[PDB]
Image: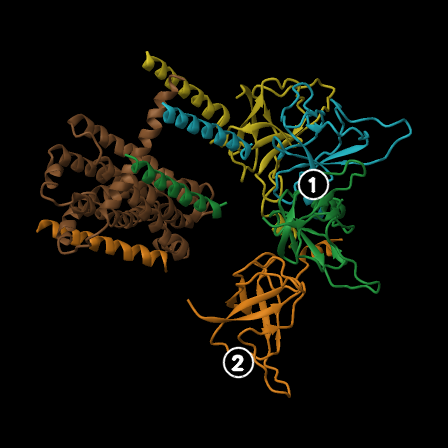
Chain colours: A yellow, B cyan, C green, D orange, E brown
Amino acid sequence: KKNEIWVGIFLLAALLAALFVCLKAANTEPTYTLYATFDNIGGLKARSPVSIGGVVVGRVADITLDPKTYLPRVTLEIEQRYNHIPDTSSLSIRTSGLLGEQYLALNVGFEDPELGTAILKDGDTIQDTKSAMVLEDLIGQFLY
Amino acid sequence: KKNEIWVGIFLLAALLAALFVCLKAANTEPTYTLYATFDNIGGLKARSPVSIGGVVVGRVADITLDPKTYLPRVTLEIEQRYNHIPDTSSLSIRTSGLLGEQYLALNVGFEDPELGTAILKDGDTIQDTKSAMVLEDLIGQFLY
Amino acid sequence: KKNEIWVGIFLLAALLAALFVCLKAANTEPTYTLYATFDNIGGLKARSPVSIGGVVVGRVADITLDPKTYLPRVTLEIEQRYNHIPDTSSLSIRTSGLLGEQYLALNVGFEDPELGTAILKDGDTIQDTKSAMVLEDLIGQFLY
Amino acid sequence: KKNEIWVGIFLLAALLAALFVCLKAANTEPTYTLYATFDNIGGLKARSPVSIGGVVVGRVADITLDPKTYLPRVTLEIEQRYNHIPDTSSLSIRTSGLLGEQYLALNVGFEDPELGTAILKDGDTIQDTKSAMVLEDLIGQFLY
Amino acid sequence: LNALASLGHKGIKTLRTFGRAGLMLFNALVGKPEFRKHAPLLVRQLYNVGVLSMLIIVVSGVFIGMVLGLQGYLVLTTYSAETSLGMLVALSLLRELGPVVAALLFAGRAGSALTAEIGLMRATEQLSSMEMMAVDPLRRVISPRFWAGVISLPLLTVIFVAVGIWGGSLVGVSWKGIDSGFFWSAMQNAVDWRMDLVNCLIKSVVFAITVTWISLFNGYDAIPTSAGISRATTRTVVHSSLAVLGLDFVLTALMFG
């Protein structure tokens, strides 16, 4: 009977150790998509912080160019519970420092027009871009 | 036996003596929580330094967005002996240089108003108007 | 066999005696504390180097703000053989880079006044602060 | 006679391997010291470049404050073939950038007096300090 | 307690084996430092433990260097520093894996099979008949084997690090597109001689004193029946494998403390 107990210790101790590597050592949310055609994505890799006012609300799950019009189309990762976004928005890529990480910092408001409030969810395309943020302007604006 | 039981008692005592001393040289504070409405925390992580005047006093042990208004609701960890703090406070996000860890250095003054002093303890959702850095607004400033 | 246990003991004793002197050097000095009133120590952690002109002279820990006047009161760790330091002393925080340690690099000099020379040892206080290693102060000023 | 052959190969194969690893990992000179008392040494560690005019000729193998006068007493490593350097010398701390090492770049003239040419060798304490850079406070006050 | 008396037998028993290990080895290396007999006698033992253990070291040595050159190549490229590969596998081999892995395989091949030859030589009473020949076997058959270990394993490590570091110079330089003159260049000023190069020997030569002693002791007090001898072989591999890691954690504390 001594061996049937000690195997049960051996099988149980591997089970606590199995949780210890996945719960403590290594550790998500179903979202909806949103299209966005840009004009310059040089430096913005996938999973960069998609943010509202700086506070992150999404990640980049799309680095692809559509091979028919040559406007970089990114599909965003905005969570399912975001249900009251008016269409009034601006889209711009920022950095968080001189060279932080080249993250997307989009603009939004509550600016209701008098033609309804068009919602922004489940795959809308936003017609805004900020192709100015380059490492070529500051070497052309400090000296010309 | 006499010598056998004495040796079994001897080695068993030193095993519990070294185990207790190993717990000694190899190792917290009951606190109160305060909510906050930080405008931008991109770059601020969990357990970030909460500082008054740079002196670290608390931890940002939360990291969660309130899913109803998207003005970020952060619970702090402030020690229980901090019982004489007025409501006059500004809460600021600093970096301790260029790329530090984007810690929280808040300000508290002694501007006592003429309505009595309002206290900051046990669940006060303190209202800050920091609106933290992007720096590219100031980039265009010297690029007039 | 009355001799094997003796050479078993002498082997195990010299095993641990070789072991103990081995762990000894692989692991300190009686100093005096010196109080200091500051304004900002954000980033200066515990065990930070006290330095005079560039060479380390102590440890900066204490970690604790005096909760009646709210000036950061820091007791230093200055060695007991430091007995002939005049009162002309300035206390400055320096980083050694953009983000190194933000250690304390205090200034002293031999500006002996015409009223004798006051000494600084064993619990005195230098009311000469540095107050700033925040860039957001002065990069906030000139940029507006 | 088979076994005597293989060992002879093995010690040769031990020797072939030993010479290869020694030459790759291991790719010195007797000198004299020269004492130097300064006013600022901040940022300079040991083995930093000691240079005349910009080319390194020495090493700082000292790093220690003279614990009776509080003058930073630094001994250098000038090569033993240097026997024609006069007393006209000015010791200056340079960085080669904003952050290289904050090394030593001293200056020596050939200006002979009317009282013989005194030499600097084998334990001389050269007296023309730089009172080196206050660089943080230099950036701070100019930025205002 | 009734069960605490079963531990009282063991606490005396397990210490008397340590008394036997010192007492056997102390008799093995005292008196008559003869060299006319032993010098051909010892060189036959280096064919036993040095030459046969040579092939397993080099064919495993190329696999460690090729893995560390492959796995290390991903970690440098995510931190964008190509030149660090030469000061990585040179660093990692010459102070961590060189003394630890080579001593493991030496306990594997030469550590076990030495213990088999000892206990078998008592099982057929070649030991017990040599006392009738009035020749003390501990200076006669043990000390040719014991010196055959501690001389061998330092020469087993320096062959291991060299063929280990050569295979590391293959997959990074040749296959994964790095200039050859750049790779050795960072390695030239990488490591010193005084606390790195001789330090590899200090970790290795203190392993050979333990593994050879722990192997040849288990052959001397094993039960001479055919059951107890193979029990002693798998007791030798498990006891050396704790002693190599029980020492290395101590010997990495002094050098880098």
Residue assigned mark 2: D84
Between residue A68 and residue D96, name the one nearer to us: D96
Report the mark closest to the observer, 2 or 1: 2
What kind of residue is marked 2? His
Amino acid type, callout 1 = Asp
- The disc at residue B137 is 1
Q: Is residue B75 above or below residue B136?
A: above
Residue D44 sits above or below residue B109 on the image? below
- How far from the left and from the top, in percent, is residue D97? 59, 59
Q: Is residue E183 visible?
A: no
Residue C101: x and y in percent read 61, 47
Q: Which residue lies furthest to the right in this view?
A: B114
Q: How far apart are marks 2 and 1 (CA)?
A: 60 Å
Front residue of A47/E165: it is E165
Work out whether residue E115 can be spotted: yes
> Circle 2 marks a residue in which chain?
D
Q: Is residue C98 left or right of residue A67?
A: right
Q: Measuring 27% from the left and 37% from the top, which residue is drawn there?
A: E20
**Left or right of residue A104, residue E224 in this image:** left
Residue E139 drawn at (x, y percent)? 19, 47
At x 41%, y 20%, the residue is: A13
Q: Is mark 1 on a helix, strand or loop?
A: helix
In the displayed structure image, the side of residue E164 where residue C61 appears, left or right: right
Mark 2 near mark 1, Cβ–Cβ under 8 Å?
A: no
Identified at 10% across, 33% down, the residue is E124
